[PDB]
Length: 61
Length: 61
Image 1 (spheres, each protein chain N blue to C red):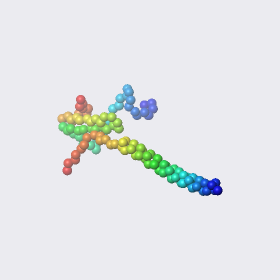
Image 2 (image 1 turned 120 degrees about the horizontal axis):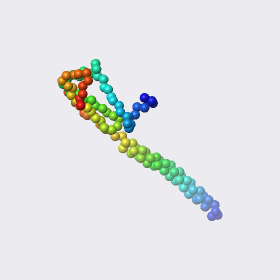
Image 3 (image 1 turned 30 degrees about the vertical axis):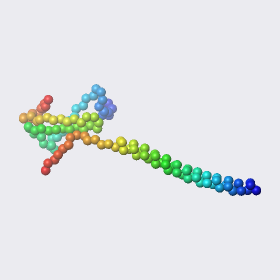
Image 4 (image 1 turned 120 degrees about the vertical axis):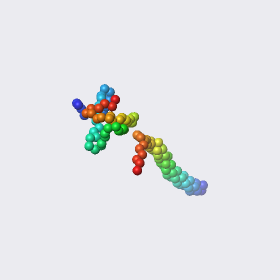
């Protein structure tokens, strides 16, 4: 008798594990992408400066 | 003279001629400024004063 039920409970947990595994698989990819953009965005900002060359000229009306 | 090189490196020496004959009018007893803006390095300028009697070749020290 005891063999029959343990099959059913066994199937229950593996399905929950797989569904949890799929969700934790799906979520890990998203978090990885966001971290990548932060480094790229940070580097671009630091290198975008501007200088002034020469004198400043006033034209009078 | 041999190749087409126009880079300025050790041992070379070049003069520059700025022609302002009809377009820009300059005469005696005047102060003018000529500004040079290289793509990198210092940015210098030249301030002089036209003599009181213009000759064919004039020296401004």
